[PDB]
Structures are given as C-alpha cells and as structure tokens.
Amino acid sequence: IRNQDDETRLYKSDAMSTFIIYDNTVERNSIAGVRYLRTKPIDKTDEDEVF
Amino acid sequence: IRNQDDETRLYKSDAMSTFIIYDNTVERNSIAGVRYLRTKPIDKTDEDEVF
Amino acid sequence: SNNVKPQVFNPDNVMMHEKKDGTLMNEFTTPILQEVMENSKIMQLGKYEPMEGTRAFKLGVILPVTKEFLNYTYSQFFEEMKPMIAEAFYKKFDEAGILNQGNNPFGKSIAQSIEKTNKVIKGDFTQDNIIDLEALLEDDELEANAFISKTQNRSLLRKIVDPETKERIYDRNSDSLDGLPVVNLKSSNLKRGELITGDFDKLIYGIPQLIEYKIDETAQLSTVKNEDGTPVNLFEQDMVALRATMHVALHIADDKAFAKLVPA
Amino acid sequence: SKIMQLGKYEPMEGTEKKFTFWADKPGAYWVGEGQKIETSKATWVNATMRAFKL
Amino acid sequence: IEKTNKVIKGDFTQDNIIDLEALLEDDELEANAFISKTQNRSLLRKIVDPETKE
Amino acid sequence: SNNVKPQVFNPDNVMMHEKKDGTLMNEFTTPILQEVMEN
Amino acid sequence: EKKFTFWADKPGAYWVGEGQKIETSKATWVNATM
C-alpha cells in the first residue's frame, strides 16, 4: 500500500482472514482479494458478529 | 497458446481433465486433444453435471 | 435417570438426537433452505432514528439443545440457526408495527393509525381504486412512497390495465405498482384482498441494541419442566442453550400518512 | 425426454436418495425488563426417492 | 393433481389460462412452464385480449 | 405470556432501569460520594 | 437551577458460614436541587 506518509509499504496479511478470487480462465489472473476482520473489544465477549 | 496480448504462453494442463486422441498408424501422430472442466456454483451442491 | 425412552420435556421444545420412538439421527444430513430468508419490512421502508438508550421494548428467545444432538446429529446447529432467529425477530417486529398483531407493546401501529384516521377504501382492485387509495394520501399533501401487499394477490393486480394507455398498470417483473415498489408480507394475518400504502418516511424506528447472542452450558431453564416437573438444569442434564435478545423502538410521526384498501 | 428438459436433475449415486428440509422456525417474545425469556423450537422434515430400471 | 383436485374446467381462454396460473400462487408458487399437445396450438393461436388487443 | 412490564422482585434488592410506573431511567446523573471510605 | 445525586445507602455485608448462601443487598441514591 502507498501509505499516508507517501511511502510504499509492505505488510503481511493473516491467512485466516485473507483470500483471493481468481479469473476462471486457464491463466488464473487474480480478480479480487478480500480481508475480513472481527472487531472486538476486551471487556465484553462482545456478543455480536460484526466484521 | 498465443495470448491476447500477442505473446506465446505455456500452461500446464490438469491430468484429470485432459487427454489426447492419436492417429492409428504406427507413427501415432496426435490427431486431437481435449480438455473438459466442471463449471459449478459454490453456494450449493452441483445442480446439473454440466461440463 | 434410568428411563430408556428419551426425556419428555414440557413444552417439547428441546432438540433431541433420539426420537420418541427410539430412532437415532446418526449420519443425519444437514437441512437445506427450501425458502429464501425473510427481511424486516419496517426496517426496509421506515426511517432509521439514531437512538441512545430508550420508547423501546425487549425481544428475545432461548433455544435449548441436547448435547448428543449437538455432537452426533448436527454440530453446526447454533451457527446456522442465528439467521433463522433474526428472521423471527423481524417478523415479530413487522407484525407488531404493521398489523398490530403479536401483542405489540408500543401502543402504536399502522393498523391503529389507519383505524383512527378511517383512511380506508372498500373495494376490489381496479385502476380507479388504486388511484383513490393514493389520492387519500395526497389529500393531506403526502404522496405515497410504497405499497404493502400479500403476494397471493398478484393474480389480481395483473388484471388491471390503463384504459387510456391500454397497458398493464402493474409491472409483474419489477414487482412495482404504478411505479411504486410493492413489498410482500408472508405473514398470515394480511388477507388476500388487502393492500396498504403510505409515506413510510413518517414511520420511524430505532434499535438501541442489535442482537446479543450468548451460548451457555450451565443455567437453569425455569420455563422448561422435566416430565416430573423439575426445572431443566443444563449442566446436569447434559445440555446447551442459545439466548438471543434485541431492543426495538417504534414511533409514528404522522398517523394520517397511511391508508388501506380492503375487500367490500 | 421432456422430464429431463423441464425438471431439476439431482446427482444420485445409490438407488435411493434422502432429502431433509427446515419446517418450523422459532418464535419470539416481547419480555418485560427482567422477565423470564420463554423458549422456542426449530423443526425439520424428511423425504426420499428411489430409482427404477428400464 | 388428482390428490389436490387442482383442476380448472373449461375452454382455452385468457380468463381460464390466467386462473390456471393463479391457482399456483394461491399456494405461493409461480408457474414456470406449460406442457401441451401440439394438436392444440391451433386453439392457443386464436385467443386474444379484448382490452390490450395483444 | 408476552408480558411487557418490569419484574417485581422480593426483597427489592435488584437494580432496574424501568420504574414500574413506566418511568424510564435514561439521562441518569451518576451519584457522587460525599463521605470518605473508612479504614 | 442545579441538581445533585448523592449516595444514601451503603450495601450491607454478612458473615456466611462455609457453603452457606450469601445474602444480597442494595445501595440507593437521593436527589437534591437548588
């Protein structure tokens, strides 16, 4: 990602929360990637499943 | 295959979905090759076994 | 206990691996959704109101499950049931707000608003009755925003054509009548020949608390009696229960913004 | 075959097939502050089909 | 059909054909296709709406 | 039941948000402690 | 106008024998205005 401080930064993405959807052709270009993350606070086992 | 961007590309073809039909003569020239794949939705078990 | 017939509960709401006849659901295939999941109509039509705290009223329910059922018959049960609960809450809240059924605590409803203002049209579905229904709103400077209908009457709507333009007033593909969107209520209370409309921006709702889910393996369910009448104890009768709760709030800003068409 | 034209196919390995569907969905209760939350219940139903030989 | 008695009596007409399709949504189902005998497209070919004249 | 008013308890030890007359305890001004806690 | 809320009851406490039931208690607050 091109950061706010205007620098090219590289960060690892956890496997349990990232995946890629590929083009169906034999070339399998990557069409789109998704990251989905559970926000949770610490005090409560915050009962709703917002991602 | 000659790619759309006009480049010669090489891709491995999956052994469980490819075969070749050879000429019957002792030379066994390859007459024709076939590839067949199971397009599917993921939201359910396959509806019609379509290839 | 030494009863070899499965535990009879009262009410019989507990999910069980073993049927009353002794059949065991081993190797049980997971069910499939024969119908699409329903969505809250008043949350769809009405205007959301940012609300902190609280009028509002608590909805909730508890589902008890036998531990054997959770282990052998259907492990993912609680994870696949949560939408089915949320559906039930949406239907309860819709049935209260729209139809005044299901013991609606708010003292407010569209049905009461219309019964108060007497904004009702007696008649069969005709282009002139659809126009009169809409004019009942435009009389008070309010313009209809949508229609609420029993899906079983599309057979009636397809029979109406504009005798001037000589074309169908009801677009069966868009499911829109006279250009306004029609939402369908699956509830049994809205009869075949009844149609409702209004400026739903005048119908305001709020949600002080989105659904909490707490799963538990240790509480007592005082409301479920064993066969002998003792309360079910989850830890001790080797059992689990899922609790769901939600708070919802309803206000009708202008009770004249709603009108109803009904068979003569 | 007009049945193969109009109907839905189903992959079937054995001579018999089992279907299971939801039937009942839980209710919901308004409860007063601190009132006991009444339970509710889910339900399913089963169906089956078998093959014949031409 | 025999167990439900879901049968309409009468001639091929826009009236009866609409009623026939409506008989399905009376159970919250929508018709998806028709099965007919090619001999009768003669009858289907000669029915027209008197209002929209289509 | 579908009963929609607050549970009366005995003894009255339970704290509640809804007074049984229908008054609802929003906006609540948090009490301030006047005394100092004793050893 | 000014408004105050003060604590008006300390919650009690009990001597509970081993495995005896612990009893409950409540605090309360009082409103004042000027």
Image (spheres, coloured by chain):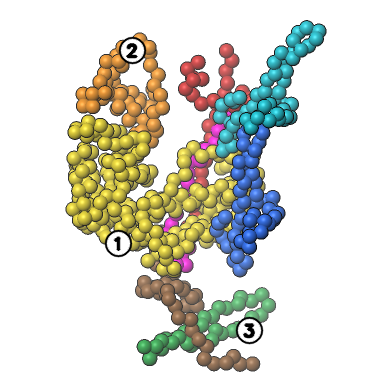
Chain colours: A blue, B cyan, C yellow, D red, E orange, F brown, G green
The residue closer to the viewer here, E5 or F36, is: F36
Distance, label 3 to label 2, CA atoms, is 95 Å
Whole-percent x, y for residue B10 in the image: 73, 29
Q: Chain of mark 3?
A: G
Say which mark, if any, is on residue E40: 2
Whole-percent x, y for residue C191 in the image: 30, 43
The relative height of residue B25 versus residue D42 in the rendered view (above or below) is above
Instruction: Magenta stretch: give its range.
Output: D16-37
Asked whether residue A42 is in view, the answer is yes
Amino acid on which disc 2 is placed = Asn
Indicate whether residue D18 is drawn in magenta: yes
- Residue at the far front in the pictured view: B6
Asked whether residue D16 is in view, the answer is no
Whole-percent x, y for residue E28 in the image: 38, 35
Both labels 3 and 2 in a single chain? no
Q: Which residue is mark 3?
A: G15
The relative height of residue D39 versus residue D48 in the rendered view (above or below) is below
Q: Residue at x 33, y 43 (%)?
A: C182
Q: Chain of mark 1?
A: C
Side of B28 where C119 appears, left or right: left
Amino acid on which disc 3 is placed = Trp
Amino acid on which disc 1 is placed = Ala
Distance, label 3 to label 1, CA atoms, is 56 Å
The residue closer to the viewer here, C197 or F22, is: C197
Indicate whether residue C58 is drawn in magenta: no
Say which mark, if any, is on residue C240: none
Side of C262 where B48 appears, left or right: right
Structural crowding at the residue carrying mark 1, measured as other residues with C-alpha within 10 Å and reported as few (<14), some (14–19) or many (≥20): few
Q: Disc 1 on helix, strand or loop?
A: loop
